[PDB]
Amino acid sequence: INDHEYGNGTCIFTRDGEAARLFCDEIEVGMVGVNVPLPVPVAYHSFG
Amino acid sequence: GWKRSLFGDLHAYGPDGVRFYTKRKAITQRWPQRKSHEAAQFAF
Amino acid sequence: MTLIKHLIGGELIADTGRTADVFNPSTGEAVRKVPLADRETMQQAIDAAKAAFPAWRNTPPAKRAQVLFRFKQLLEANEERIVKLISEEHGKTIEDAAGELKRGIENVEYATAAPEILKGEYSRNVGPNIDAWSDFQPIGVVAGITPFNFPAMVPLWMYPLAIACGNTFILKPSERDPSSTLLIAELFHEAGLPKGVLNVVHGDKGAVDALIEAPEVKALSFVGSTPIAEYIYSEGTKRGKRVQALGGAKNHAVLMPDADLDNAVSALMGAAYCMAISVAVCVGDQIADALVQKLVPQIKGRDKVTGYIDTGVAQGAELVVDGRGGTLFDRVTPEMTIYKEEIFGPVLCIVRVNSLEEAMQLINDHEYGNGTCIFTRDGEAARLFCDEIEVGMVGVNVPLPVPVAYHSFGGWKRSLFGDLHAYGPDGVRFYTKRKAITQRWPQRKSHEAAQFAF
Amino acid sequence: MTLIKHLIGGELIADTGRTADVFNPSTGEAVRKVPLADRETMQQAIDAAKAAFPAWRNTPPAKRAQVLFRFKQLLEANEERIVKLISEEHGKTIEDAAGELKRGIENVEYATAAPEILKGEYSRNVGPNIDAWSDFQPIGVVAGITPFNFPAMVPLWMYPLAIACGNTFILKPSERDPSSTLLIAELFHEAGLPKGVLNVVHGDKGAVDALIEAPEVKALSFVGSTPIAEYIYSEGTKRGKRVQALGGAKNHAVLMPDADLDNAVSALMGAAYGERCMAISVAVCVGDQIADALVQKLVPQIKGAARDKVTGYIDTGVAQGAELVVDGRLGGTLFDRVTPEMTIYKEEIFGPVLCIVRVNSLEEAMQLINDHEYGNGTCIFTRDGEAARLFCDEIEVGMVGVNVPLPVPVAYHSFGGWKRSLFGDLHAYGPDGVRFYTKRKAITQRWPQRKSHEAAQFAF
Amino acid sequence: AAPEILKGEYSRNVGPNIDAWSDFQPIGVVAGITPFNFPAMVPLWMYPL
Ligand SMILES: Nc1ncnc2c1ncn2[C@@H]1O[C@H](COP(=O)(O)OP(=O)(O)O)[C@@H](O)[C@H]1O
Ligand SMILES: Nc1ncnc2c1ncn2[C@@H]1O[C@H](COP(=O)(O)OP(=O)(O)O)[C@@H](O)[C@H]1O
């Protein structure tokens, strides 16, 4: 996810607390959803 | 667009530095429920 | 063998009558004698405090703050002297004893700022020629009964706050280490405290029964063992007194099947052989069998204890490691005596249970303590545990800074180890009464000398 | 004619078993029937509330505030209908009944803003990979037992706040006027409240004992008479429950020798003979002069089976040596020379009765008031500043009036450490309610790490 | 004093059983290339912050 022109929303689906914490820490997307979708109806990458 | 002043008042132009070295993150979280929490529902 | 004096009415009294000995636990050798006081010697203190109250109640907030601030300095001045006195009669690491006093001083620092949060409102003409105001007043003469562990901090957690609120105090400390407590009392008098505002009376069940009976004393504050706590709570409350009571209890850790065992074992090993934990509730047999497997190797480093262990075996618990320390019991149930009765020393009990609901119900349905942990990788489990458990402080895969387990009785509840700024208001409310005054001075038509008195 | 239904689990249940009658004085022609519920019918409610709790607990603060705000509107909409139902089964001026509901609505308005004062703090990495936070949580399922006077306001003083904090509620109101209470419950459901969050179960000592016994209910709240209050307090607390209890009592006025008599008489006449008042039943007079003078002024103005209770009360008074100055046989009754050893001082009586107690000092008057189950209001009448200051300092009653009566129309003593004021400023005594219906928690959290996160480390 | 202005908000149950929060995180590994004039101040203007 991080190595491409990353978008404006991402989710992780899991029951593990440690996984979720790590995902939220190291992912570079600005909005993150843990077992929940986000109100971001179109994907965009931001330049500059 | 990542602009910093070198000689301005630090308290005035410091936030620009802070914004250059940080990223905002916005988390929404839910732990979806189970009906029961007997030992059979966890691992080894 | 010198003799330790009472501190009634501002001066040191020597009592000779009933009398026990203070030993030096690491030297096994009796060092001093302590006077078990009669009802007359207590009535002295009560009368002294009753007398000091009206003056002290009307002392300005800022002056009360002032005397407390100097009290804090004079403690930070005499630390070395104090700590020596704790380690000598209680027997504890000087580093621990100094850490205790640092906490006591945090309690004194909090009390210095209590006058500020106690200011109330005034309103001229809330109605026609009717003023209204609201105030927080002290309740009167109050007493505190303190335990063996913590002769420095537990009193400093009671009386400075109560005195800052404008009450007067009778302190009946532990017979077994009363010298360190009394020194700190004296330093308070040296800081400027009026005579009678703090009194120290040494004694035992007699002394305590005296305070429970005395109708002048309005509130009673106790930390110690659960039978004595229940006593003072019920018998105090039945006589119209306010009672705050912390009685010894058992903190529980919960292990889910997914628990990181080395993490749980680290907490349990630090806590049982830091935090106080005496029961490990395991959900499912797998995690329990596994926990035992790891605990046994590492558990290799009074007549009360043999009786305790023996009863356990008798009622069907599995004695896995016999420390006769370092004792481990498995297959323990809440109907056993080893679960119900609290024991001094390194003893851990494993209780096997089938669901998280059962574990939480187990912890909630008994005299629940002041700390609890859950060990798990599951976010949903942890959230649920934190929501439905009734213990005030919770640790998720981490132990808590709660070194002794206590249950709190009644409605006048105070936390001993919480953040002072968070649980301080509960103390303030215990030592004060709220008042709402509405006032009018009904008018006369004329104010000639004939309308007044000679 | 009609029969009143329970409101368990969001639907109206019809119970047929034991049953009493709701009467309507001044007619005393019985108008409806009420179902005295068994333990089974209560366990229904308990299970309903226990079920509703987890969903409700996790409902957002703003959504809870929202449903309360509509509840306030639907009450201000149906006022006429409600007040009618109060005056009909309790028997009181519609103007009083409407003033009661106005108070109940103030309680609902306060509850709508409780979610705001309830948010807590968060700290990421308070230690290495250790988060910490503090929360104010609801306690679970709670119950409230309500009296005959105020079938509208006393419940609205309990459950809206408890529900706003995120608990669920079982309400066991008075058998004698339960229709008005139930209507207001239904309006709450109509405003949007989930099923099971509020339940109404009619009954009596059986029903109450059920709630005292049920280990699921975590807090118990009561307003009524002193014997029943002591009961619920002690028996509740002994079973680990939180108990809030207001029991009927007597408010005292003190008259100093210098008191402005017309001012004191005005207060006493409004309080004892004249729900839109103060409640005062005892006038403690310091010195005989002011007492003789007070009696002189009071007597003229007091001319403006079930009966057997009052005659018994008065007759005992005479028997034990009190001076019966005005015999109201019910009209205004006045007793003089009353002492705390008499039955007329110890036992509370329905009706317009004032007792004068003569005492020699202010200290004695204060000790008299403080040494009994002291009420929720007291007055001192005097011109002396020092007396008034001392009275305000040493009296233990929470609200005090100096030459002025207080807006405290019924006298109650408060038991235990979970203390709530019924008639205080809501914004001032509301936090005590909030603290009774919540528990503080401090959480510290760490998710212990793995070295690698390959699929093999998770479950299917 | 930069840690102080960097604290974020937490909200329990922003939706049914849904918590929300916001944080200000560091970005990772960063580099600074400094000039001849000011070998003291220009680096201290970059890396400490
Ligand atoms: N039987 C009793 N009744 C009332 N008070 C007691 C009784 N025994 C001890 N105390 C007082 O209670 C305090 C501590 O209670 P206790 O449970 O004995 O704790 P400890 O573990 O320090 O002995 C002591 O200060 C002691 O004087
Ligand atoms: N012996 C009893 N034990 C417990 N509760 C009772 C008993 N008798 C009556 N009650 C209940 O107590 C509640 C109020 O008590 P009471 O003092 O009768 O109030 P009121 O002032 O309305 O007469 C009622 O709702 C009633 O069901």
Image: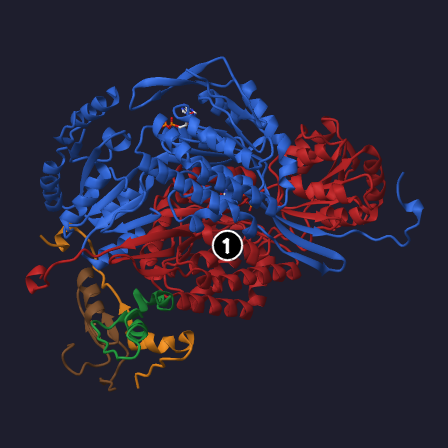
Chain colours: A brown, B orange, C blue, D red, E green
The residue depicted at 32 percent of the width and 34 percent of the height is: C94
**As drawn, is D7 to the left or to the right of C275?**
right
x 46%, y 47%: residue: C424
- Amino acid at dot 1: Pro
Vertical order, D308 against D12 (above or below): above
Q: Which quadrant of the view contains residue C150? A: top left
Quick one: which residue is furthest to the front in this view? E37
Q: Which one is in front, D135 or C190?
A: C190
Residue C156 lies, with reference to residue C89, above or below; the image says below
Image spot of residue D245 (x, y percent) = 51, 44
Q: Residue furthest top?
A: C17
Q: Quadrant of the N terminus of chain C?
A: top left
Residue C306 pos. (x, y %): 20, 22
Secondary structure, mark 1, is helix
Question: Can residue D332 be seen by looking at this rendering?
Answer: no
Residue that badge 1 annotates: D431
Query: Where residue D148 sits in the image (x, y, percent)?
Result: 56, 49
The quarter in which the C terminus of chain C is drawn is top right
Mark 1: few/some/many CA within 10 Å (<14, 14-19, 20+): some
